[PDB]
Amino acid sequence: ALYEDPPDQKTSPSGKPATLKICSWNVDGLRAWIKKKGLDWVKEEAPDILCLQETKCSENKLPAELQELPGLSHQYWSAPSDKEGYSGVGLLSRQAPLKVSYGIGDEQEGRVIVAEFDSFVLVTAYVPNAGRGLVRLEYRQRWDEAFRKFLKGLASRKPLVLCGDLNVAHEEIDLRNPKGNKKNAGFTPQERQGFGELLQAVPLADSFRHLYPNTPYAYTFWTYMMNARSKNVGWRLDYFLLSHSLLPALCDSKIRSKALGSDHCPITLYLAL
Image (cartoon, rainbow, N blue to C red):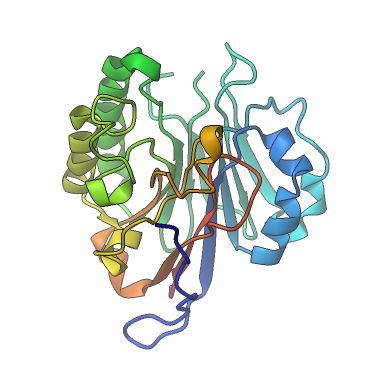
């Protein structure tokens, strides 16, 4: 029914110790999440890189409590220009990245930050949700294709880490209501197969499902309504996708189901790099 996350495995299969803690989190409103003690939690988790989705906040209004994070001093923020209080992503890092990109060619959306580091390439994404009653599904389908082709061009260089709200639960084990949902945004057969296409084209592996293939009831999102988080009626929408190149460095990929602050919970990735 409910889930208790395994302990942090901080050594790789080869016996090497992890040297890179990456944490992603859909804050569903960066200003609210901050007031609900999110920064205090990030400080305790002490990641080398923090990725944030659905900031819903222009760079104008970015709270200066963020400047109070010196272990994540290098901060980059993407924001849609048309609609305020919509979408937005952010990347905070201990080290400065070498190259910093935004979007995937077709630009205005504030969904994708791409950061090249010394050994790898990190992408954060707040993938468009199909919408209640599938109003945006046919857009998400073109998004899935675009994201894929853009990403396969980046994996021609360094290995890839892709994290963020991917707004799709892959298999039935990834949600608690598989059968009452396959006509609802996040578990339709188009979205489900587009995520497999993603794993195939680039290619990539689901870090968490690699190490925990049978583990059910492990969700990263619960609707606010109907005390669903109390009942672990949730979904796994937040992912750490890894280049195959990188799996021998994969120490562990976590779900921080107990950190409050948003409708989504944090995830954390360890790489022995």
